Every structure is written in structure tokens, then in C-alpha cells.
Amino acid sequence: PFVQLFLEEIGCTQYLDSFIQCNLVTEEEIKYLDKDILIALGVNKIGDRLKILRKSKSFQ
Image (tube, rainbow, N blue to C red; front, side):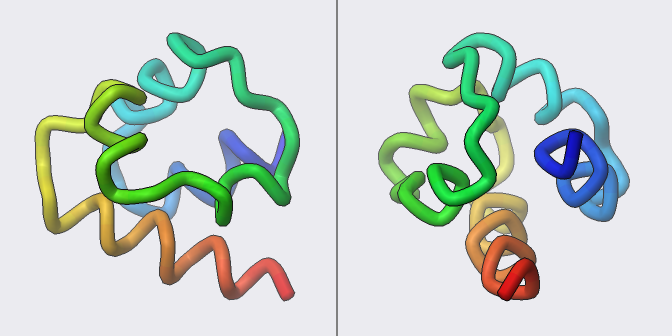
């Protein structure tokens, strides 16, 4: 799924596991993720959080 493929661009699949923790499969919801939600998602790097939001925009 795109959720796993775009996240792979970060270079660390560990975050991919973070998405499984929330069980998020909708691509639009990725943009819906806020920096605070990413913390709950299971992300240990604040810089990567910015990458997820910016890369998600690339979807459109």
C-alpha cells in the first residue's frame, strides 16, 4: 500500500510499524496526522515527523 511505500522514502521502516500501531490504512489520513498524533503513532524522531507531512503532500 502507498502508506508503506511513501513512508519507506524516510529511509526507516521502523516508522512503518508505528502506522500499524494505529492501524491506519487510508492515504488521506496520513495528511490528517498531526505532529502530536505522530508521537502517539510511534515516531522517535521529530525531524521524520516533518518528512511524513511533507511527503504526504507529494501524494497530490
